[PDB]
Each structure stands twice: as C-alpha cells, then as structure tokens.
Length: 514
Ligand SMILES: Cc1c(-c2c(-c3ccc(F)o3)sc3ncnc(O[C@H](Cc4ccccc4OCc4ccnn4C)C(=O)O)c23)ccc(OCCN2CCN(C)CC2)c1Cl
Ligand SMILES: OC[C@H]1O[C@H](O[C@H]2[C@H](O)[C@@H](O)[C@@H](O)O[C@@H]2CO)[C@H](O)[C@@H](O)[C@@H]1O
Ligand SMILES: [Cl-]
Image (cartoon, rainbow, N blue to C red):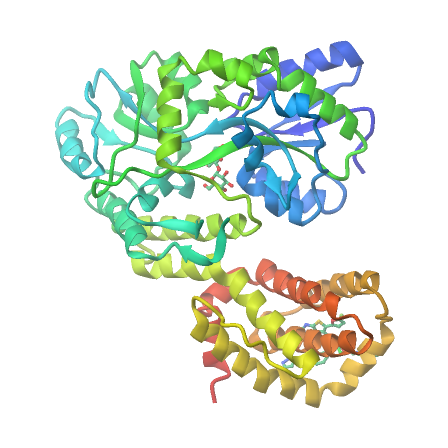
C-alpha cells in the first residue's frame, strides 16, 4: 500500500512542519529520496485507522502518550538504535517511548504548558488561580480580560484538574485506580466552570480564539506550549513565560508530552526513516531547523538541549514539567482523553453538572478494564468449571453483580441457542493459536455489523464463553485471555458512547435485574 523509495511524514499543524520539510529537503540532497511532510487534521485519530490496513505515513509524530495504543495494535516497527545513538538523547526521553520493554519511537522534545502573560498589561502575573476573578474584574474596566486558553482540548485544563488530587492512573501505572471523579478533580473543574459562569472565560473559547486574543493584546494571559512562542514573537507582544498558578496552594500539574517519531510497521522504507530520524532530524542542525519554525521545548538531544537550556522560556517550561507528571503511554490513554474532553466541554457549556460529567468520565476511563475483568472471568470459569478466587478491586460490587447477572443470562443464551453455537463452532476450524486470531477477526465483523442493545452484547460474550469451553477441551487454555481481550476490545471500541449512556455495567445489572 505504502509506496517504496519515498518518506511520507505526519506531524501536527501547531508544530514546525516547514522546518521539518527543510530537513526533508537536505535528506533528498544526499539520497535522492523525496520527503513529503503532511499535517492532516485529527492525525492521532486517522493514524491508527489507516495503519491497521497497512496504509498511512512512514513516520508519525505525536506526543508519546498515544504510541502504546499504536504499539498494542502492532502499528509500529520496533526501533533499534545502537548505544552510541541512545547516549546522544536523555535516558528519561527514551523511557517515555518504551512499551513492553521495546523502544517504539524516537523521542524529539519535552513539552509542558506554561502560563504566558503580557508584561505591558500584567507586570507581575498571578501566583494563584484564586486571584484571577479579581484580576479579570480589574482588567475588564480597562477593556481587557485576564485569561483565555483553549477549553476544547482537556490537555489545557488538566493542570488545574490535577492540582488538588486529580489523576488519570495512580503510579508502574495502576489501570484499576482512576482519579478522574475524586474531590480534587471536582474542585479543579468546579473552579473552571465558576470562571465561565461568572463571565471571566467563555465555554466556546478554542485554540484559535485564545491565540488571536493574546497576540492582539486583548487578554493578559494564555496557557500554551513552546510551539506557540513563534506567533507571539511575530505579534511584538512583550510576553513572559512563567510557572502556572497554584490551586488551593497546590501547584498546577500539567501532563508532560515527549514529541516522538514512530515508524509505521507497514512501511517498505524503515531503513530510510531510521536514517532520516537518527542522522538528519536528531542532530544540532536538524532540530535547529524545526525549532526556528516552531519551538520544540526541551529537546531530547543533549548536545542541542545544552544550548537552549539557557533560555528562561525553556527554564519555565522545565519548571512546569517538574511540578507535573510525564504522561502514561498505556493503550487506555486514548479512552481517558476522550472521556475527559467530553466532561470538560459539557461542564463548561452547562449541558451536564461537574458531578454528572466527571462520573461519565470515570465510567469511560475505567470501562475497558471493568469490561475485561467481567468478560475474561466469565470465560475462564465457564471453561474450567471453577470461579476465580481473586478479588475484583475498585468498583468490585459492579464487577461481582455484572458477573452474577452474566452467569444467569449467559448460561440461558448458551443453553437455548446451543444448536447454532455448535453449528457455527463446527463451521470454523479452531485447532491452534493462529485459528483463534482468525475467530477474533470474524466476531469483530459480525458484532460491529448489527444494532446495539444488551441482548447482542450478552450474545457476543456468551459465544466467547462457548468457544472458551471448546478451547479448554483441545488443550488451548492459553488462547482464552486473548479471546477475552478481543471481545472486550470490539465491545468498548465500537459501543463506548452507548455503554457510558447506560451507566456501563450498572445499567447491565439493572436491565437484566429480576
Ligand atoms: C454466534 C452467532 C452470531 C454472532 C457472532 C458470531 C458468529 C461467528 C462468530 F465468530 O461470532 S458474534 C455475535 N455478537 C452478537 N450477536 C450475535 O448474534 C446475534 C443473533 C444470534 C445468533 C446466533 C445465536 C443467538 C443469537 O441471538 C442473539 C440474541 C439473543 C438475545 N438477544 N439477541 C439479540 C445477532 O447478531 O443479533 C453474534 C451470529 C449469527 C449466528 O448464527 C447464524 C446462523 N448460522 C447458520 C449456519 N450455521 C452453521 C451457523 C449459524 C451465530 Cl451462531
Ligand atoms: O487534549 C488531549 C490531548 O492532549 C495531548 O495533545 C497535545 C499534544 O501533546 C501537544 O503536542 C499539543 O499538540 O497539544 C495537544 C493538545 O491539543 C495528548 O498528547 C493527546 O493524546 C490528547 O488527545
Ligand atoms: Cl455555565
């Protein structure tokens, strides 16, 4: 699918893509390979869809948080630099692109949100979120506003949500302990909604609108990354880059990104991508090219980071980096952000309350692990005759009642529909691991191509139980957890919005409740 003798690169449109294309041109110089840089809308969403069919770009650039998802789905080549090259980048930048002990990308640069302020409007920027309503009242009398930043991407609101005890996954990383709807997070997002309610911010404010307002000198402050600094430089606003305000005395905790370059597993040009990234981009000359288009932040390349470390804007970036936490790269990061995006937009717009909205985000962020636990437990106890002794952990009442419900309703389906199950199981030839990976592909297709309701969800999980019974029978128990993950995966990928609407597994318990 991907053309050979070429490199197609995706990078996000807020980055220095003209600069990366200049590195592209210098690679063409030496090698006669053309390099196309593109910056599609929603490339973090489009990359996994197209790569899954052996398509998309050779190289994708994104923050490291998405790359584990991509790696889990087998969409990235293992990268294998020598020690000599590894030692040119900071050990911690490598750690951000390590998934199941394999390097899955080249780290490029460390990114944290800072408070950006207009020195001519605000000589001393505020130290606390609490003083911003006063400062806004004061600035409005002079025809200005205190603060405008992008309220459409949860990334920009995360530092306030994290400040007083909000977290995605507790720290390796425990995917059973999600802190999206705890007191700390409610307080953070409540402060934001109050700012909006009291007219100190507008729910509809996005990246464009905030950027234009700061750069015309209408607002005294914005929250943004190093990529933003080029446009402000050009607007001749006298700006400073500082530490974010505290909330309830606690520092703002930004989620730190490492801009990372992955190589599509479907690429016929992997050697070229490695050569480009290792010997063209990740050089003093290579990164300088890009950094002049749009600043990268604290670059991963020690040699060039020593140069830029002297910049007080980088020093403030690093200061904000250390008050915050480096993002997880676990596959569930994608579901976490989709849930928290939706919570922030609906709290901001008043379509839900803070409590309603963060509850729905807690369900969304937990949904995959909650679903896997129930489904894999049902499959294993169906196959073996014996229930799993281990405790269900957090939200363990929901898992226990869902499993107990599924036992009654799933046994009923398997009993009544045994004919078609034996029939469909015989029509397929389950004999080995490779046959199991095939069966997954079919279920995904059959489930996906039909209406959403609890009966069809029980039927998918009940057929899985049926198949798990058989897999045990042919000494193939090892393939039962992969089968559970496949059923879990399609269920929460394709029916996420419906499951959150039904209050997830509590709705399942309620719907089939005697
Ligand atoms: C299990 C199944 C599904 C089927 C899946 C399947 C097929 C093959 C693989 F790998 O997954 S995944 C899946 N996920 C959800 N629903 C499925 O099937 C149902 C319909 C259905 C289906 C079967 C049993 C109970 C069934 O009852 C569904 C039911 C019970 C209560 N409410 N509902 C909607 C739905 O999609 O609505 C299915 C789909 C079709 C099926 O049979 C069609 C007839 N066929 C004739 C030839 N013979 C040799 C084999 C059987 C069967 Cl047996
Ligand atoms: O809004 C959630 C979003 O946050 C991060 O994306 C950042 C990115 O890291 C930055 O490089 C810059 O481009 O801004 C983006 C936010 O608009 C996560 O990396 C991303 O996965 C997530 O969707
Ligand atoms: Cl409101």
